């Protein structure tokens, strides 16, 4: 009906599509605000006639290759997950295995065995013990000396007939009757996202396929293994590509310089998506690269067996399921009725010149009077290699409905462009990519006289949050800001955060203990400069950008007599904005709105959370 | 009985002594390892007859001024104030109150003064508009404000309430309340400046503005202040003053710090940190020593009688009475200790730079022809003090065949104010040498100590000094650093006392000032060749997890041998104050790591096989 | 994967096959060690699309004759009868049922016949006016009578009920019910004589008076009877008969016992005990075989199809279909038994006294030039049979390096009737010789078997043989005796089946008969030279606890080395039917006891240390 902090609860969220023969499966997720829980329903849709059947309180659908049956997960309260198998015809099901700590399940070609990947920890009640690095990872909790577990599960007898473990952050996939195992390669310390060793495992014995390469195995058609990466990388920020390995490594993407978002191989054909200029598009490789779905949108996921299906999300609509027969046909409209009565604001794309480059930019125009001006919010995506674009961004439609101009850009370092365009940001953070945004703003103001230049706020999460702190220390233009799970100091990010030990050396430069860049590019040392009211938002479970990042910056700013507030969420990780409990997320949305309302649209003194939140 | 990780559970811990007339009240606390809980039993003794009655599962005893009745607390999740007639010990639930930090009797034996706090208390998120965002052992402030309740114990109602800013305190003075509040300039000045008000019937009058002391007690005629009238540094020795309407310092001739003190009918009882001891004195208009020697007086109370809790290096506290002489009231742990070997430390003086410093060591039972390894303890601080109190680890490791050694480097409490102030901005320089010197001198008096094996451990500042040691020195063969500091800058912007404490102890303009990076172990991490164990807890806001974890992460990035154990619960003091099962595990770990990385080295550390 | 105490939990156990039209249904059972529970899942297979569908946490599948619906039970302490539509498997709850032992469809695919029991159910005490006071696996009778309910599954009501004496049974015959009730003279004669009635609408006529068979099945024109018309000994082979109102025995020229039988459309499907095998046959008016080989057919059903469970010495049952050839329907354990080694027993013939006997032995993997210890297993009985079924302990111990050796002594099932009758009042005489002689022939065949370590073990009658062996012989270096017999007199008076069984197998006039003392191991106890482990369970009324405990106490009084393990739960059959955790402990115990007293003898058995 109207846009507010709850409206997101009214959307149907689709995820994790799967297909075999003429069947499609996916997960329907709702945010239940009353019970404060997410509900999951696997939907199984027959092609031809649109008929649906359901598996309630379940997720991770996997359809057996023979299309006779489907495997899934139910989660528990008692804190344990169960693996179930149901027959596809009647949907009667049985409980196969009770498994905690299971991150994935994949069918074998025989529609009998499953491959489960998971982890084991030390699990002492009173304390965690760590001999390795890092001590934690975001959304995974404290590693507590975690290792990777592999289970070959028989769904008939319901037993684990094979099990072995590997180092932390390994992964595996079926290759025929054998398993392809990717283990992060270790020199001084495991080199994550950089180098892997790859093995071929069958019946307790393995052989090494690759030594210290830059790619890992994401899929197999049983003849060929699909490799995701480059064979070798100078920078993890380099565009990931895809390779087919028959015993020779043949890259099919060499001519195309873009990063591969997602890929799957079936029957020698390879379906994959790319980041391009704010979009994520779907292509097929039959031995030539062919276009499938390309436009202003993001393809969130896809699967192909006899048929090709994918989820398509847009700037104004959450994902719906589509089928491609050689023409695109839309299979589901879940949110059709809600958005019939709900106004959406489409972003207008513009080009602008910044230094030596021409960049992409977008703004949303609220409804205002021909005789009046509107306040502006500048969003800055996480990164640096994140990308803004044609996906669905809640806050943006929210604030547009409330009368704000919405403006965002893809500064150098962003994904969706040339590899070089991305690498440029390296040890450049806060210099050129910040000018990119200021120039994007300026071109925007010129395109839109009705935007009031005197009220312009800025907000961002993660890297965006760092950019928000930076913007307030380095510029006079912003009347308000909201910084979330950001970075005020690069050094602690290097030592503290989950990925800090590798990522920072690359993005901020080497020799962190010495290198003066770390204090030079960090907003924390520029604190005396901030003249704007600022809200900091953080979450206690976020190991990507740890609590200190927000809290130090807040404490110091307060010591300098600045106006700043900190909201610390008791639960939730780095992604808590989208992934936290519905009630949590709602309160954040309410806070986000109200701050921009009282600090930007019209400035008023102080912030009273008790009175404001009701 | 033998010494191990479980041995601390067998001790009776006494606390919070109280007296009115001839009656004595105190708390008996046992650590139950099975139920993994602490058990509290209020014991009430008749000064004669030795007779003991009890109040089960309760604490915070307060005896009425008329000694007819006693107030106490029972904690569940809510706390309840109870009142029992002392004669039959029959009791009634008076007020059910969560977040009450204290209770005190009005002179009339009717009204109570209860000092709590109120917070925003949203379930999903905390919101902070003030500083700091948290305090160690108090949790996240979440906009905390101080509350004051005047409770009538008869009708059982709250007849008065008002609130003050965070960290405010109050006490009874006659029929009014003395309210001390932290003074605000930009941010509240904690431990530095206070405004003091006198409060009655809704109206207040400001007694003091921007003073370095606050009101710690009253006899109702006079007000006892704790602090100085003005301080250039918080690290200055805190003294006592009698305010009758004119401030009079009674301590002006003694340069020492007061630990504790109270006023009863014109007379002032107090304790001082002196050279590794805490001694009890009485001021009747002259300073007269009551209990002095090698020990700590951990608490005391006096009305018609003077009682106190004495604790020594070989023993946990017991209750003592003094008439003209000392008489030991209770032996709780005697039977147990009869069966347990105890080690008295040996006092020794040493030369460090220009000063003569105190030192101590404990000598194990050693084979006539053999040498023993050494464990160096560094106390919290900088203004903490080692001495004659009871340190579990020391006894434990002693009975385990280790040399125990510790010193009081400059900056330590218990000496001249200047002796303490010397450390300011000097952290890791002079005091470290003081430790290096004390060590040498020790090795000299004890040739039996094996210089080839010397370890070091410490908590908080002691943890920092441990880190510092392994970066600055090839002397130590291993270390255990608990809740310490690898980096001073974050200690400034992150922890609870950082904003002020760091500026004074480290330097001003922290963002610029290079001292923060120079005295910070994290930058010297390349220099560490000794195996290190890093210990932390998730609830400690004094020295946040970043201090231990960043250090551990960096060291691992450099290929050093290091380990980290992070306790899912507990604050800065979790080692002593953690849950029994928690504390035992830490003891067993502490124990095993010194065994395996120091006494006889070995490769790797397996916490699974080693714990059980 | 490796063989150990826990390996049995990795196998899928199928039971209770049923079929109608093109449909098949059976029960999948798994032993869950973590939850310590047995899990059942009804599996329904279509012979059309070769597909599976499931009914979770359920058993007793019964498919309606028209193939449209399936009835089943869910237990938990109640039980409930459900009905599901076979196409979608949507299910509705029909009747909440306590004490229902069986359910069967009427030809109308509407009504069920439930047979069950009712007792006195006093909370504090059981009261018994009949015999016996208890039955193994049924608990104490407490006055129990058999109850019969006719249930309409549409309206979900009991339309008909009546009751008969204890141990009565019934089956549908057309629209009527054939009731078999035990014939009473002084006490009911169980397993000897029955009276048979035809019951409809509250009315009954008597078909048979005091006959030695009862009614097993009906095709609605014909009643299948199981027994003989007249048996002198209950140990006589039970045969099958067809009653159209004249009685025709179909097996007359075959002297073998029928294990199971069913009748559909004038044809009779049945199994036979033959020489270690249980084989499937059909009778179309001439006996013709279906599945014959080294195997046991554990169950079967026929309507439009013939399906059966087949189990072998190396594999648990899998399901098969017979179209005129055998086709394997299920391999549940196939993947497991790729990675798990199994041992096919070698069959051998030997001579004993006047007979030629069957024997089997498993040869372990041995270091050549060295020898392996032996374990003789004795089957229950005496009319039990060893053979081609799957015996866990045998696979377990063979994998641990033991020879396994067992025989069917005279009195065993699966040979001529006279062969079975030979053992009567002979227990411990000839059949024990049969075992000794078999062992001797085996030692010849396997010179690598070490005759200086040979153990012996058995359950029930086999525990009897184990006791007997240690008192009657010097051959054995150790033994494990489970739920056996030391003293026959108490077997007769105390045990569930004693009053009839012991008169037939041991002898008549039990109180006056010297055989009861003479064949009892207990009276020879002074003879035992070999360490012995006794195993019992408190719930076994087949061989009551005194059997093990008296033998134990006596042996101790004589200074012998003996131990006793008493399982707090479980009946006679607890080794297989006990709770998974229970069964695991039993296995671990069995294994470790043979290891430490047989393979290499050591002093003492410390159970707290030996099992985890
Ligand atoms: Cl299956
Ligand atoms: Mg809802
Ligand atoms: Mg199951
Ligand atoms: Mg990448
Ligand atoms: Mg009351
Ligand atoms: Mg002080
Ligand atoms: Mg019903
Ligand atoms: Mg029979």
Image (cartoon, coloured by chain):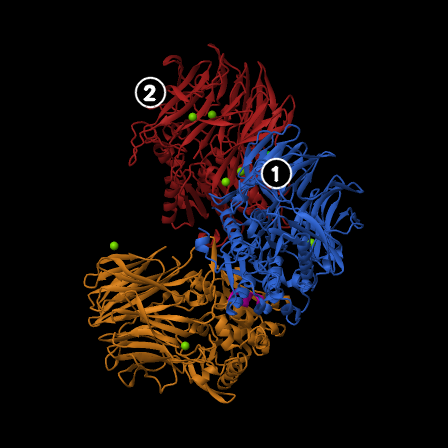
Chain colours: A blue, B orange, C red
Q: Quadrant of residue B117?
A: bottom left
Q: Chain of mark 2?
A: C
Q: Chain of mark 1?
A: A
Relative vertical location of residue B83 with respect to residue B432 in this rendering, above or below = above
Asked which secondary structure carries label 2, the reply is: loop
Relative vertical location of residue B4 with respect to residue A316 in this rendering, above or below = below
**Category of crowding for the residue at label 1, using alpha-carbon neighbours closer than 10 angstroms: few (below 14), some (14–19), many (at least 20):** many
- Looking at the picture, how far across and down is residue B352, in whole percent? 51, 87
Residue A563 in the figure: left or right of residue B314: right
Find out whether the residues at labels 1 and 2 contact each other: C-beta distance under 8 Å: no
Q: CA distance from mark 1 to mark 2?
A: 70 Å
Q: Which residue is mark 1?
A: A26
Residue C454 in the figure: left or right of residue B207: right
Check residue B554 for magenta coloring.
no
Q: Which residues are magenta?
A: B544-551
What residue is drawn where x is 45% and y is 46%? C532
Examine the rendering and report whether any part of residue B595 can be seen: no
Residue C129 in the figure: left or right of residue C593: left
Foreground pick, B124 / B4? B124
Q: Residue furthest front?
A: A371
Which mark is on residue C185? 2
What residue is drawn where x is 63% and y is 41%? A319
Tally the numbered discs. Answer: 2
Q: Could you tell me which quadrant the N terminus of chain C lies in?
A: top right
- Looking at the picture, how far across and down is residue C32, in whole percent? 51, 41
Foreground pick, C11 / B462? B462
Asked which secondary structure carries label 1, the reply is: strand
Which mark is on residue B165? none
Foreground pick, C310 / B283? B283
Labels 1, 2: front one: 1
């Amino acid at each position: 009906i109207e846009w507010d902090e709850k409206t997101f609860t009214k959307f149907a969220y689709l995820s994790d599509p799967r297909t075999r023969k003429n069947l499609v499966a996916y997960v329907l997720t709702k945010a239940n605000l009353e019970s404060n829980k997410y509900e999951n329903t696997i939907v199984i849709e027959n092609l031809e006639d649109g008929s649906r059947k359901f598996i309630e309180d379940a997720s991770m659908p996997r359809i057996s290759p023979d299309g006779k049956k489907i495997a899934f997960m139910r989660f528990n309260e008692k804190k344990t997950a169960q693996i179930w198998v149901a027959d596809l015809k009647t949907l009667s099901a049985k409980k196969v295995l009770e498994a905690k700590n299971i991150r994935s399940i994949e069918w074998n070609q025989d529609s009998r065995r499953l491959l489960a990947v998971g982890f084991k920890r030390r699990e002492d009640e009173d304390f965690i013990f760590e001999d390795d690095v890092p001590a934690w990872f975001d959304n995974m909790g404290f590693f507590d000396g975690e290792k990777t577990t592999f289970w070959v599960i028989d769904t008939e007898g319901e037993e684990v007939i094979e099990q072995f473990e590997k180092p932390r952050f390994s992964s595996g996939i079926w290759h025929g009757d054998s398993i392809v195992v990717s283990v992060p390669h270790r020199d001084v310390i495991p080199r994550y996202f950089k180098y892997w060793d790859i093995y071929l495992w069958k019946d307790g014995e393995e052989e090494k396929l690759f030594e210290k390469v830059s790619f890992y195995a994401i899929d197999s058609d049983g003849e060929r293994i699909l490799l995701y990466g480059k064979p070798e990388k100078k920078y993890v920020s380099e565009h990931d590509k895809i390779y087919i390995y028959d015993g020779e490594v043949k890259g099919i993407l060499d001519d195309i310089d873009r990063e591969v978002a997602q890929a799957k191989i079936r029957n020698g054909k390879v379906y994959f998506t790319l980041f391009e200029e704010g979009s994520v598009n779907l292509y097929l490789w039959d031995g030539e690269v062919r276009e499938i779905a390309k436009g202003k949108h993001w393809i969130m996921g896809f699967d192909a067996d006899e048929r090709l299906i994918y989820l398509k999300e847009t700037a104004t609509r959450p994902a719906e399921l589509y089928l491609w027969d050689g023409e695109e046909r839309q299979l589901t409209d879940y949110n059709g009725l809600i958005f019939k009565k709900l106004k959406t604001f489409e972003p207008r794309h513009f080009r602008f010149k910044s230094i030596d480059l021409e960049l992409d930019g977008w703004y949303i125009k609220p409804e205002i009077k021909e005789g009046e001006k509107a306040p502006v919010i500048v969003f800055v995506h996480g990164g640096p290699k994140g990308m803004y674009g044609y996906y669905f961004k809640y806050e943006m439609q929210l604030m547009a409905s409330k009368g704000y101009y919405i403006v965002y850009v893809n500064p150098r370092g962003s994904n969706g462009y040339s590899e070089d365009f991305a690498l440029r940001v390296l040890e450049r953070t806060g210099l050129e990519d910040f000018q990119d945004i200021l120039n994007g703003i300026e071109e925007f103001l010129r395109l839109e006289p009705q935007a009031d230049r005197e009220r312009i706020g800025i907000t961002g999460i993660a890297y965006g949050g760092y950019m928000t702190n930076w913007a307030l220390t380095q510029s006079d233009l912003f009347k308000a800001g909201i910084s979330e799970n950001g970075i005020s100091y690069w050094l602690t990010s290097y030592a503290f955060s989950d990925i800090g030990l590798w990522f920072d050396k690359e993005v901020i430069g080497d020799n962190p203990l010495e290198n003066e860049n770390y204090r030079k590019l960090s907003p924390l040392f520029y604190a005396k400069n901030v003249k704007a009211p600022l809200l900091l938002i953080h979450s206690l479970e976020d190991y990507r950008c740890p609590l200190d990042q927000s809290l130090m910056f807040y404490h110091v700013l307060k010591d300098l007599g600045k106006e700043v507030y900190i909201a610390i969420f008791k639960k939730g990780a780095h992604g808590h904005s989208i992934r936290g409990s519905p009630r949590h997320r709602m309160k954040r949305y309410k806070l986000f709105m109200e701050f921009f309302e009282r600090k930007l649209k019209k400035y008023e003194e102080g912030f009273d959370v008790e009175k404001i939140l009701k």
